[PDB]
Length: 90
Length: 90
Ligand code: NA
Image (cartoon, rainbow over the protein chains, first blue to last red):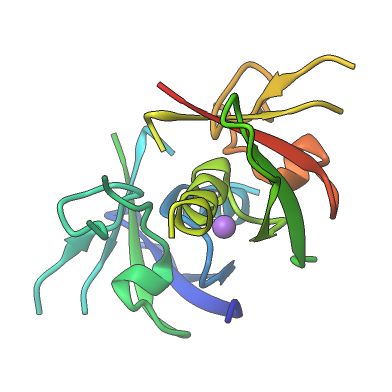
């Protein structure tokens, strides 16, 4: 099943408040990044991280991808409603 | 709004019947291709085409992409419920 969820986005080293972003569990990471950018600034240059003790970079295709490698969604990483994400540029 | 739809997949030059595949309008092309491959054979090596007079290759990122370029979904191309798609390899 596909369903909406909200993530809380921290813009790294900017000292600003976390920004809520409405995303879908079936959104690929690139779709998540586009929704974040649209919201925050109302994808190749930006990095998205999550800390479920060890910080993890979220990407469409990485070494964790379902294995031919299947595109990662928030559902793949098991990112749940309310999760904190970190956005950084360059 | 996000919603399901079924596409009818023709496996090019194999002389076989069209295969129905359940997809989502918010599925990127790579997500669509994965669902097609899972169904047909129960993404980089496969090509997906649609004929709304002129045949068009469907891809995550192409020259038609929303312009930084946003990832294509079936919703982007305006592929509706029942649409015929053509799958070819190499
Ligand atoms: Na999606």
